[PDB]
Length: 274
Length: 12
Length: 99
Image (tube, rainbow over all chains, first blue to last red; front, top):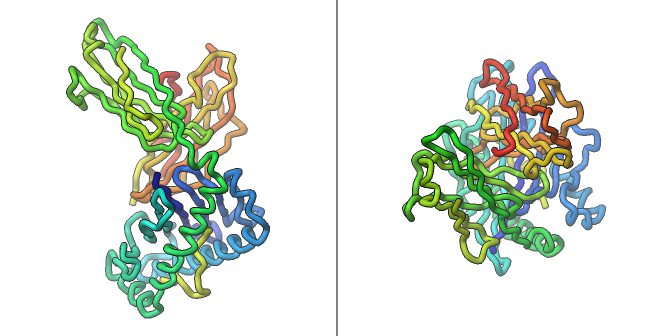
């Protein structure tokens, strides 16, 4: 189908505690493949998926240099923003940055992304035309004018339409056996009695990839949300994902309820019934 | 592959 | 600006006593990123616990997976203890084999 590459950067100032901590992680679809930690001993970008290890030493030198440079700039930017917002030297603050690109199933560029947040709220983001910015407030407007003057959108557009998608395509080829797989959910249902009057049905999806899935309960063929519980999709730790959905039903009416499972790895959606 | 910036890119 | 963690404690595979497994504590939806997550065995902190690299979702909330290999038994109770600025006392979530 379509695929994506994303980098996620987090810088946190640690006032009194020393110098800011920087963490970078890279993903293709729902699979992490690199990390960099400003606190770790290696001071290198590190592999976190098997297929990225077939990149040679120049790749690791270059990605280490560039991600270190990004970390240094975000260190600068923590001091800059505390000035812009008239904040004290005392509190801890957070810069988050996400960027990346999507490709379609034939590998062609679909869209590119760059967005930054300060203390959890939108700060500045590149617009979809990859030529202009959306600034969230007056402080971000200061940054906007510096970046429009420096033609920074040209650099971002060049990367997002060029190197980003070219390397994303390369990863999908190098990691075809895992990135281009679909693992269909392994499903089952559990049944536990609350009282004489009610029971819980819990509909499970396990060992699936990618993470996108839909679990819905119906009663007599009608969608049901009352007295249901859906948990957030969660990692199993082995590269696959898990989810469940439960419903509280009157005892002896279990046959009226169906759980419906939709996932890319299923030719047709599944219906489970107790 | 991370963004390849100018030395002075992305300064707030 | 301040978001309290969602917490799920669960096994990688459905638990079978005497069979090797992985105990997971997944914390998500939180802000700021400073957090302590400990896995407990009968109230005692488990020594060797690993975690994923800090990442976040579209809405800027952070998420982390803490995990350890373990072998469930009839007797042993497991839980996850989460310490975060939004919580006046750490939240302890017990492992339920069917959640």
